[PDB]
Length: 161
Ligand SMILES: Nc1nc2c(ncn2[C@@H]2O[C@H](COP(=O)(O)OP(=O)(O)NP(=O)(O)O)[C@@H](O)[C@H]2O)c(=O)[nH]1
Ligand SMILES: [Mg+2]
Image (cartoon, rainbow, N blue to C red; front, top):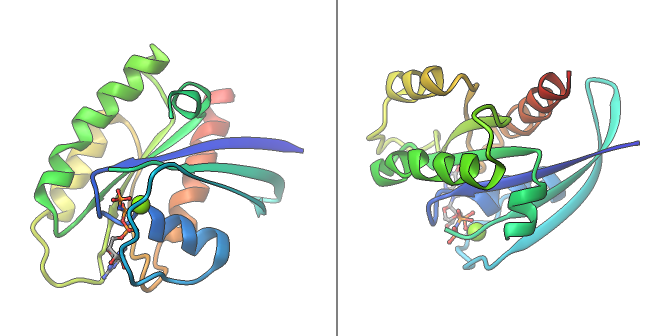
């Protein structure tokens, strides 16, 4: 069996824990519990490949940062600053990995909310510059939660080629 080490990064409160908890335990946590360094493991079938997902839910670990094979760079569509911080998280990932091509996926969370300040056009333009997919998600309605994590694994498969 193949293991995939995934790291979820992003500014505080964008929904990193809610996205991971939806993927692992299939429910939406409505309360805001401040995360330190939560880890998770889960057996799933992705495109027919049985694989283990080792997921670190970082706070807004250098071990997971060095061992991480793919990175979910998450922002909230109602949080302009979190979208701006994406550049800083990507630079740190490229720094600790010393690679200009690191498997990443850009996630715009909280797309169920009507208080948007980051347009879909902005995020797709940013993702186009990075050469990474962009997924709109809602941990509340579970929209795009599977697609976000599964697309990251496909990006890892493409990188391992
Ligand atoms: N409406 C809505 N609320 C969401 C969504 N995702 C998370 N939230 C809410 O936003 C708050 C923060 O979510 P959380 O998962 O804790 O964010 P975080 O990125 O893990 N925070 P931290 O970096 O401090 O650990 C919670 O109240 C949660 O219910 C979403 O898709 N839609
Ligand atoms: Mg958290």
